[PDB]
Image: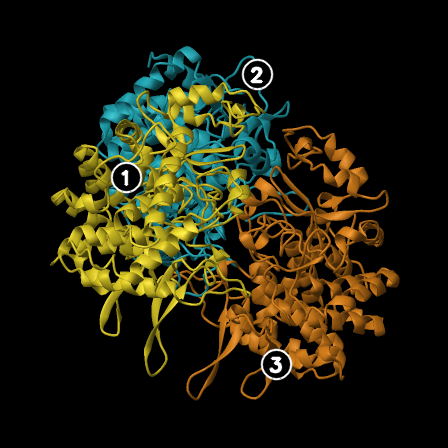
Chain colours: A yellow, B cyan, C orange
Amino acid sequence: RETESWKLLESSIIYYEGNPIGTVAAQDPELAALNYDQCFLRDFVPSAFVFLMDGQTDIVRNFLIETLTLQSHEKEMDCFQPGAGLMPASFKVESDGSKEYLVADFGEKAIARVPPVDSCMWWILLLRAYEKATGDLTLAREPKFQAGIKLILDLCLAHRFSMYPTMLVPDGAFMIDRRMGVYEHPLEIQVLFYAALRAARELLLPDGDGEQYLNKVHGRLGALQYHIRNYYWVDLKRLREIYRYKGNEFGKEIANKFNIFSQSIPDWVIEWLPEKGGYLAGNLGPGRMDFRFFALGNLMAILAGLASEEESQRIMNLFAHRWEDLIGYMPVKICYPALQGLEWQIVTGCDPKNIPWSYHNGGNWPVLLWLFTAAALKTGKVELAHEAIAIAEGRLSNDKFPEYYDGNNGRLIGKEARIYQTWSIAGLLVAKQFLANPDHVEFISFPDTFIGPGCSL
Amino acid sequence: RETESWKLLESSIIYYEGNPIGTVAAQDPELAALNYDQCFLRDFVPSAFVFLMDGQTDIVRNFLIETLTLQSHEKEMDCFQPGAGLMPASFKVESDGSKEYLVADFGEKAIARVPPVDSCMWWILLLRAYEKATGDLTLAREPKFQAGIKLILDLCLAHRFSMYPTMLVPDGAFMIDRRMGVYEHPLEIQVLFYAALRAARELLLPDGDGEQYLNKVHGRLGALQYHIRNYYWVDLKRLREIYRYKGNEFGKEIANKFNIFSQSIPDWVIEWLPEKGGYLAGNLGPGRMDFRFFALGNLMAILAGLASEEESQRIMNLFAHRWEDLIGYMPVKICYPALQGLEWQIVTGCDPKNIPWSYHNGGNWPVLLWLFTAAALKTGKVELAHEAIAIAEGRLSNDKFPEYYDGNNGRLIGKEARIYQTWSIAGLLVAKQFLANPDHVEFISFPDTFIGPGCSL
Amino acid sequence: RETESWKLLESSIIYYEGNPIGTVAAQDPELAALNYDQCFLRDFVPSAFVFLMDGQTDIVRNFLIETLTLQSHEKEMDCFQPGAGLMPASFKVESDGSKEYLVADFGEKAIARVPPVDSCMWWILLLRAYEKATGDLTLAREPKFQAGIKLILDLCLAHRFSMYPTMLVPDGAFMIDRRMGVYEHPLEIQVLFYAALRAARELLLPDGDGEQYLNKVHGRLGALQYHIRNYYWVDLKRLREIYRYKGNEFGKEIANKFNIFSQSIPDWVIEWLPEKGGYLAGNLGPGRMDFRFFALGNLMAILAGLASEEESQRIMNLFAHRWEDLIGYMPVKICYPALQGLEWQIVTGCDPKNIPWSYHNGGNWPVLLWLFTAAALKTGKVELAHEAIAIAEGRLSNDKFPEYYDGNNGRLIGKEARIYQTWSIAGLLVAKQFLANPDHVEFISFPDTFIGPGCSL
């Protein structure tokens, strides 16, 4: 098309052996490209959607094929290898004088050696998205694709010492790829885990051990939805219960299973919730409940069908009631609130890129707009999608599509934000296209809600 | 006239050799006179305007004469003598049994030995105000008066080690005559400096060396105006620039010339600014930008013609938007916001007179109403002038014209505030007289703005 | 000589048109040279000393000549011009394809545009030192060198508003060249000022205007010495007096002239002082007394003859008693104590280079060894000189002569310290040569004391 956004997206494309295989993170002129000249798997997802909806589906097919190939690459740090299923954080095309080849990062080159746990889950979801948008059922069912999914599921469904059906991760294992107190069981990983499992339920063949994987996938989905809906869910009713929990309860039939001390609960949470509002908490673990609202996990939980229809409503009500906090001058705030003062020091380790209301620490991210629009249509709240898109559209082009925005409400352009960030551009585009045709939402969302009050099914 | 204020103003007058030479700072019966029995040069400025607009020009003339003589006095502290162009802070009439004589304080008697830098600049502006109100051009031209102006310009245009066109001062060198972190290059000094130059530009005779002075003045004005307007000016656009600045930039052609670190931008300012608001920062120095709003300098910027017409508008826009912060229960707040807790300790040296939201540290000062009125009229916003005067007339008389008011909104009478403070009284009168005849503003302001987009002219 | 240090110093030499004119600040292989490839005037002083004591004096003669040429350079920022006497911070040799020329920085390129006020003062002291070292009395007495001295004196003795005979400067005006709360009247500037006046008194020719300067100089010196010694001097007796000062005292005949509130005296200083110890305060200003111990200013005050025989002993007594703090693992701690927590934030503007116990904020500086050794010799405390060198010798070569050390006791190598820092190397060399031959101290010191118990003489 003729729009500026379309053109930038066009010039972001990375070509391999004459074929388009992905998009760069950003096209910032002044700043050295550094790591951002690479194609990040998570960053590509919204790029892919734009292409899938525009009809040109080769680039997405190529990407899916090369990333599956990259899974096979030898990946080692100090003679230690991770599970074979691991997908990379990013990749770029490098060439010696003669020929071209793909160089990836699986965390071994990454800053703080963060592991891209979310990438393999996005890869599975992006595969489904390709399948539903195009109708091509052959690709996912090719042997190499079936094998790779099972490798991913082998990792995801690996055994634990723990009684939690959730996935244990170190800090910075997802979109937040720096130290932000999102270690242990962050919502985002658990929601993408659930969704990637729901995806696998569709894409997998019962042939061979296929029969066995679907049985594991199925059992884990039941436990995961139950665990997440029962223990992560926050609203006034639930908040009143927790507040009155007694400490140091021992046994099976007890209320305060995770030994959350009520005095630990922050003061801001009680005021913040509207009567009808609610959300899924950012984390849960031994003696820990992270009450910070995380946007992606909560929005995606609606789309994945993990949130009940009412829970989905109560999330959007909170968005309506705390519009200046969650959207403000630029949708969407990555999480709320920011860690401030000494809490910033301890939890981030004095990370100067995640100072309060900046970047991961409560910054405002354009890319999340597509999650937000998709979740709003699905909940029958288009007015909110219109307002969000209007707000973003009013600034991005003028501000050259910054990577992120800072401050309580997003007034500031991100402190170290790259300009011409691809998923900021693609974010707007994807949101407008969902707005134009709300049936496109179907490839990233699930028609039914696959949940229950029981731990099984 | 029969108004209560006129009578108090008239009883405030100081007589010398049977002649009216000035007005006392305050007439507090209960409090010890201390130094408030003296006549301060800056406190007299608003008193003078009352008289000028009424036609009683003798007292102003006499003041201007006696102060010019006072300049030529021998002032010394520990065998050190300052520039001979130094005007005193205050003077009183002392008499031995036999005869009357004039004793002055140039800072050698002052608390903390603070230098009255603003005083010599006020005298000039007052001198110009005498002309424009009266039409008498003989007093400015006199040999002594032209010499005194020159002596002042010798000081202000003294050579520096610094590359800043601004004036360097110690702490507490103007209306704020105490340690308030207004050391170095404070807005008030720079604005009064700029304004005194424009006045001198008109009052100077080209005869003799006058031409040499005229060109220096003309040169400095162009450099100064460029410096203030480009580096002190704050609005949202500018704030987004600074927040994204890079540290430790080196060389002639760089963005962050003064090495401001964005993490040091206080939290309050970004929410505080309205979309169309703006103001001049309180100070600028090496690695330092004081984002506190200072009223006098900002309002006097409008009057002096330093602020452009649009910039003037953005200052007045701020007042409407932050009316409760900047006016509240008593116009006008001297600066916003207050230094609090540990910041108050460090910056003021635990000064108990300046505790948070008191006195210089965010107090509300009745006198500043005349600045505010003059600028409101000049900017074509009479309604704001009206409301400010009403708020003041609502309390002043009943409160017995306190020197200042305290609190976030000036709800309290100043902790150690004098009652029957003369420039609170004169401040209200001048404002009302301005309101009756807006043309009177012209003798404290400049109709034209002497500025451009470069350092020359 | 054949020592490792002598060769590192040789490599550092900068050649202009086939002549040695100065030395680079550091020779770090890994770091980009940046501003350090230039020759800083202050950094060269110890380098110059090594060459004076070696016998090769032409580099120093050349340096004095080329820097005097620089003084004549046209220097401006935004159409504004400082005094002609301003000496630059640093200079470097630059070439076209075929021509060599000198490019200096007078502050217009400097980080935070800080003014090298100390540079012009060092220039004078060095010239005297050169003269005393060689015997060449033609150089200083040349008509260009008499003019340049006069231009510096013109700036330094410029007229003030203040009643303080000290020199008023912005923050970062000396060796500490960043925002560190050393604005106003920092000890170092006043001590270097005193020292530079004494040098001019020796250097200046009486014929022509020379006599006029000598009289201004003489009178200033008398005032300055009285001012510093009476108001900056800290000991237990003085502290007890100030602690009992009354606030807000007004007039000429008062104890608390500067309005120091006792509650603002830090807790650390009372315990820190030994009974017979004493030192000069870091700063004096309205309502302000900086009690931080500053090393250079205090050590140099001994050499310059500003400090009395007893004051000098008490200063060295303090060093002896607080050896762990002031010397620790690397002489000498640049100032004590470090600003911490919120005080670091406010005072430095969150400057990440001057975090607590790092760099200017209480770092340990090897270059100060030459000051300390020279002073310990002069005071008859050679044992202290031996010990300081011993400690320094123990690590400098192994650590590759870092720029500075960090920590409470300098245990850490400076966070962003350059290796092969020229004046760290020269620092150790100068100290050793002084030890080997103490009579050399005479060229950077004054044999006589020029201090009076009265303001005059």
Residue located at (49% from left, 30% from top): B360
Instruction: Give the amino acid type for the residue marked by disc 1 in the picture.
Output: Arg
Instruction: Check chain identity for marks 3 and 1: say if they share one.
Output: no
- Chain for disc number 3: C
Instruction: Give the amino acid type for the residue marked by disc 2 in the picture.
Output: Leu
Could you tell whether C156 is left or right of B368 in the image? right
Coordinates of residue C306 in the picture (x, y in percent): 75, 56
Q: Is residue A50 above or below residue C397?
A: above
Residue B261 seen: yes
Which one is in front, A32 or B264? A32
Decide: marks 3, 1 in contact (CB < 8 A)?
Answer: no
Instruction: Using the numbered discs, state the Cα–Cα distance from disc 3 to disc 1 in whole angstroms.
Output: 56 Å
Residue that numbered label 1 is attached to: B314
Instruction: Using the numbered discs, state the Cα–Cα distance from disc 2 to disc 1 in whole angstroms.
Output: 42 Å
Q: Secondary structure at mark 2?
A: loop
Packing grade of label 2 (10 A; few <14, some 14-19, many >=20) is: few
Instruction: Give the amino acid type for the residue marked by disc 3 in the picture.
Output: Asn
Residue that numbered label 2 is attached to: B31
Coordinates of residue C143 in the picture (x, y in percent): 59, 77
Extreme residue in the front direction:
A208
Packing grade of label 3 (10 A; few <14, some 14-19, many >=20) is: some
Which one is in front, C37 or A342? A342
Residue C43: name its quadrant: bottom right
Q: Is residue B98 above or below residue B132?
A: above
Which one is in front, C78 or A445? A445
N-terminal of the two: label 2 or label 1? 2
Could you tell whether B233 is left or right of A284 in the image? left
